[PDB]
Every structure is written in C-alpha cells, then in structure tokens.
Amino acid sequence: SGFRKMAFPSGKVEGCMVQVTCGTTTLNGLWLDDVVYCPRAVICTSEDMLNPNYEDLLIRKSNHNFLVQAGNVQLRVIGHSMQNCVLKLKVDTANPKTPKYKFVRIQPGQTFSVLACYNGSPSGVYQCAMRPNFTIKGSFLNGSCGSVGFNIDYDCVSFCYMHHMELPTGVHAGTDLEGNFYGPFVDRQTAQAAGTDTTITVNVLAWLYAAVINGDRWFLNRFTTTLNDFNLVAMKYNYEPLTQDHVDILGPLSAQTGIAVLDMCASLKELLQNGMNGRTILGSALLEDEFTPFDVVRQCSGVTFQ
Amino acid sequence: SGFRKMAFPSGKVEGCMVQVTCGTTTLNGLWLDDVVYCPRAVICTSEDMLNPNYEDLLIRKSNHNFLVQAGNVQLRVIGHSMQNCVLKLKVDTANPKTPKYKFVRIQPGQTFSVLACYNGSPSGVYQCAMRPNFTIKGSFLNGSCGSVGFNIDYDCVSFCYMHHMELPTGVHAGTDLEGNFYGPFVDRQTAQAAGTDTTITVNVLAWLYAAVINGDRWFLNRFTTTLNDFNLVAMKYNYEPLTQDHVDILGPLSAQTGIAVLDMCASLKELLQNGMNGRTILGSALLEDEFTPFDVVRQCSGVTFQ
Amino acid sequence: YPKLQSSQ
Amino acid sequence: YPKLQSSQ
Image (cartoon, rainbow over all chains, first blue to last red; front, side, top):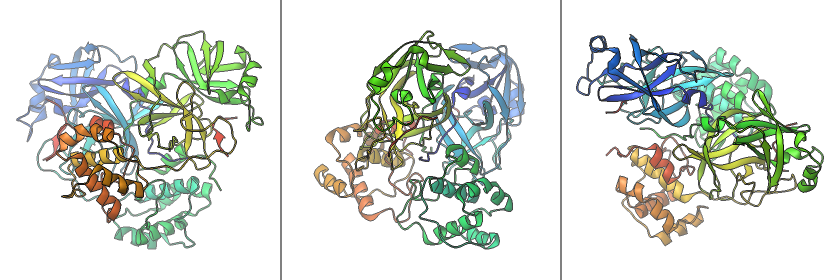
C-alpha cells in the first residue's frame, strides 16, 4: 500500500551526464555513444542573450572551442552540428555506459522523471508532468540547462525532455532531444509567457482510482453522469475536456476497481462542486493531476483492498 | 525556482541490489563488498509467520539453502550470520559496483530516499521522512522487503533504512542496516500498531522558508511569538515541540531570508489557527513536513528572490 | 495484522 | 524576462 510521487531509478541516465563549456558558459550535456547532446544556448555570450543568431554564432566556432568533461576525463570534440535548438558534439570516445535508449516527443499530460544536474553532476531526481500549456513545474537553478527528463519502459531509457529556461512565472520550458521546444517558446531572453494552464482531467481520474485501490472510497457517490454533462462541469473549473479516448485508457483501472469511468466522473464533479470539506485523498488536500493511468497501474497492486 | 519533493540520484544504490531466495520466499538484498544484507524474514515459512524463532530457524539452514541472484549471475554463499533482524550472507565475490558507503541510524524527522525494488530489480525512487512514531509512509507491495533508504552526502551513500513490513494502517516499518527496528516493532505478524503520530514542526518551518526563498510571502505576518507560547499552540494541533536546537538549525534559512525564526513561528501559528483560506504554498493545500532544513538549503538557491 | 512484505 | 539557465 501507499502512493507516492515516484520517479524512475536514475542510474542509467546518471552514466550519461557530462559538462559542456563554451567560453565562460557552462551547462550539462547528454553523452550517448559518441555524441554529446546539449542546448545550443552554450554558444551564447552574456550580452547577446536578447536576440542571438545561433547559425551566425556557431559558424564562428571550431571543434576545439567546445570543452566537454565527463567527470574526470576531458572528451575531444571531433565534429559539431546544430539541430533545431540542440547541438550535437561528436566526440572521439563512445560512452561505455550508454543504455538502450530512444528519443520520444511526448504529449501534454504525460509524466516523466527529471534528473536535475549541475556541472555534469546529478543532484536529484523528481517526477514532472508536461502541462497542457507545455511548461513543466520543475525545480531548477542556474547551471541546470541541459538536464534531461525520461521514462524507462523495461531497460530502455526514453528521453523526452532537455531543460533550457525558466519563464517569469517560475515554471520551466525545454525541448525534445531533437531540439524542438515544447510550446511556443524560443531560446532567447525576449518577452515570453506561458499560456493559461488547465488541469489534466484523465490524470485526476486515474489518481482517484489509485485512492480506491489503496482502500479509500469516501469521495465516491451513487450518481453517474454523461460524458457531455461532465465536460460542461470540467470547462467551468478549468479542467481539460475528457475524451472517449481518455475513457478507454482508464479502462483497466475501471475494471480492477469495479467503478465505471463515468461513475468516477460523477465523483469528480461532486468534488469540484463541493470541495473536499477538510478531507484528504492519498495525503493531498488538492486534486492531484501528475499521475497518468499508466503511472497508477505501475505503482499500485493488482489487488484493490476490498 | 520551483520546489519539488526531490530524491537522491539512485544509481549508486541500484548497483547494489540483489535477489535472495530461501525456500519459496524471495526478497531483496543489498550487496556491498562480499556481504549481502537482507531481512531475516527470508527464512520464514508461510505458516510459521505468527511467532517464528529465527535463531531456531537459522541453525537449521546451510550456506547452500540461500540462493542469491545478482541480475544474471548467481552468487555463491560462503557464510551466513544473523545480526538483530538482518542476515549477513558472505558471498565469494566482492561487488565491483560497491560505492563509498556508511550505515547510519537516523532520528525521527530526518528524510531519506527510498529505492523500491522487487526481485532485486529497482522499480522507482521516492523521498520519505521517518515519522515521529517511527513509521514511514512509503509505497510498497509484496516483494519489496529488503528495499533500502539512503542519503548521499558527496559521493558517500549513507544507508539508513531497510524495509520489512506493512502495518494495518498502510504505513511501513523497517530497520537500520544493522537490523535494529525503528520504533517498537518486531518482525512477526502478531498484533502491532503504530503509535499516534505528530507533525514535524521544524520541517514545516523549513518549508515555509523554502516558500519565501521561492518568492512567496503571503502567509507572513507582522507578529512574533515566544518559543513557549508557540509550543503551547503546537501541542494543541498535534505538532512536535520546537526546541532551541531546532531554532538554531533553522539559523541559516533565517539569515538568508531575513525572517527571524520566532517570526516564522508566528506565521505558522496563524496558519494553524486560521487555515489557508483556499490558498496554496509551494503547490500544497496542507502544511508540508517532509523537508528538513538541510533539504531546503540543498534544493533552493542561495538567492531569495527579493 | 502486520505483513512482512516478502513474496511467495 | 525568461532566463536560459546556463551558468557563468
């Protein structure tokens, strides 16, 4: 029993973290086979941060302008190229710790683990969701640029996020590992702001199912709702529309608990309309939305505590 | 910016996890140098679980009754002994992945990372506190016995918890790595219950300081309190007494933010007496108590966002 | 009753 | 303004 905001074991990623310096600017890179991936902002200088032309900045660089440190050892850069907002530094040594890996671009609402790093050295691991407005609510300081987010499926690491920047609201924006930003953001310090965010409805429902699996049913009720009528309440409370696809995805959790998806929707509607009245669910006084249906199934038992 | 329930990177511990089987019972062990540490409950049989005599059960075993699997490879047990509630299985191979490590017995209120494991294979990592009643609110299923909790200081892993059992309230009980239980619990399935728990006051205060470092001051007030008067409110709300030692430990966070410790106590008193009135602090609608003052300093910036 | 969380 | 979180 119990239900925690659980991250994936980070060891396979720890072995891939390096330090990249260009000039007086240092950040983290990701060393897989003989390629180091890092944010192209490493070639920025502290005064050309408003509107750098990276193609222009990069053509003025040579392989030896990039200093890559893998803990003890310096790695020799033997080639470099830019792909969207990331640099690919070819090095002369294949990382002997390279895991089985993929690059994946995730959808908003999906979760991942973040290995926060400074100067190529991991500091901590935590679980994130990609928000519907394509920010993440991370924990990041200067030097964390290049830290990566990932999922592990069996022993394959699916990298899905590389960290670039902090927006003025204190939330975070970054790219896939091909350098394409999530959201409308760009890697320059001009005025940019996150769009209005919403709550991830399918995740809130998954977490209510987690609560039931863990022996807690106080929020349930005898009612049901139609999908349309639920979504009319969802919109009022700044929740994402729930789709038939979401209903389908919540299928396994519905079957394990015996609570129809639309019945759980009726519970959520009541929670949205009444609040919790000083009660908690799985240790939270708020409706939690950073657990996917897959996360719940992964962490919870196949028995439901009847 | 941001503030997350952050775990330590788990790689150094992942390399130490093995599987131990005796008879039809399997659980996890911890392989450091040529010794595997695991709960002595591995020598239990499913019917002698109420009141096993472990000294009696163990003297009836030989080295070859213990099957230790380190992923692919089986490890040969060449000696065994019992120390309190753990077994030490000497194996003929020193773990080549052994980190720098210590065994530490922690105080209630201290936090640690848990690497949850099944059949010697890590599944997830999360951050825990030792509760004042010497339970932890973990996330554990059958097979997780032997999973360990730890802190990392520089590159030294301080192991502080080995998981043994789930109490009827769904919270968890275990030992230090010398096999001594935290709390009054014993490794047998007779009636046992956690004592009444309390909230870790010094941690709640540290987390309020985290909130201020992260630019949020809404809960502050112009008042102060005496230590005695604060503790009289603390007792009423089932909070731990705050000591002068706690005040001292909160010194660095007080100095970084410019908020006297007893001034933050006045803020907490007001929050306890009034509630939050539909507001949140660092994304929580409850007062969070699983961050130590050290945790806050580690995760937060040295700048406070004035 | 408390459960020792080994597996069978 | 947004901050690219490299270090100097």
